[PDB]
Image 1: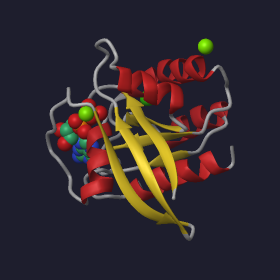
Image 2: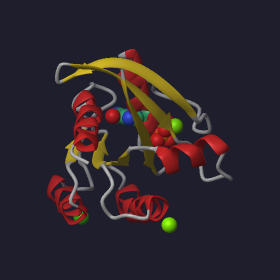
Image 3: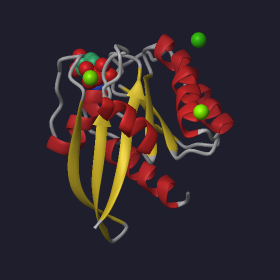
Image 4: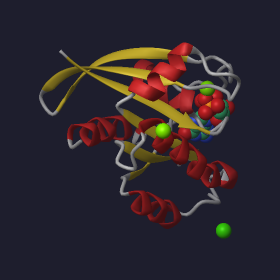
Amino acid sequence: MTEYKLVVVGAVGVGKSALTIQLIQNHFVDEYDPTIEDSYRKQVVIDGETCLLDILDTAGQEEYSAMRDQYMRTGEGFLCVFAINNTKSFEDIHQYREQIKRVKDSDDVPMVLVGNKCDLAARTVESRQAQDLARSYGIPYIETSAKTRQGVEDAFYTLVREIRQH
Ligand SMILES: Nc1nc2c(ncn2[C@@H]2O[C@H](COP(=O)(O)OP(=O)(O)O)[C@@H](O)[C@H]2O)c(=O)[nH]1
Ligand SMILES: [Ca+2]
Ligand SMILES: [Mg+2]
Ligand SMILES: [Mg+2]
């Protein structure tokens, strides 16, 4: 069975854990320990292919585990997440991308830019702003809501499809 190693990165509070838990449990967690970092597994069929997603939900910027290092080095694709009502998290994307490019020694790394919490009113980051950032990286942009599930499968499945074009 094909396995796809995905890593979810982005600022604290953007909904990395909520997105991951939504994908695996079909539930929205209103609070989830911000320090728990763990990998999760999900068997899924994507475009007629039965495959396994191996997803590290990264947490914190304390000194990385061997596992986090391993996932950064061996991860095949990255979900770079900000929240549409969190301008700083969006501005921080640059750093997460620079980090990924550094670890992969490449500017050609499967990656999807995710604008999460799209169920909330009065966003401070416009869709077009994020579209422009993603375009500058040569990557897709997808809006999601871990709360309503909108876009959540599309974000993870698009990243699989990006890995397959690699
Ligand atoms: N309204 C809304 N809240 C969200 C969404 N995703 C995450 N949250 C909330 O934002 C906070 C941070 O989420 P969490 O998954 O811990 O963020 P993490 O630090 O990136 O792992 C929690 O209170 C979540 O309930 C979403 O799509 N919509
Ligand atoms: Ca503005
Ligand atoms: Mg978390
Ligand atoms: Mg390097």
